Image 1: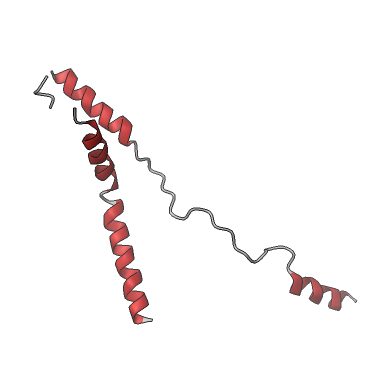
Image 2: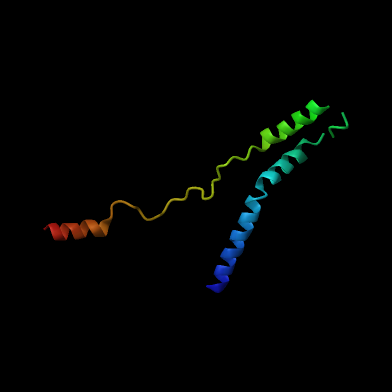
Length: 41
Length: 49
């Protein structure tokens, strides 16, 4: 049960620190998909 | 060039578009029916009788 509760806490931590970066992660994903005047590049 | 940069930023913002709504749990069905509640129906039958 202590192993399970540690796993729960770590999963919760990773979920929180992934939701925080979610918006920037998807922005970066679309920017990578969007890389092809040169000043804009 | 300033408008080009603004247009690119708006492209990124439009495509990302992550909303203030999050689907945490997708739908899964509880395999045990919520109706009829067999035990309470049989108990009510007993007590009503």
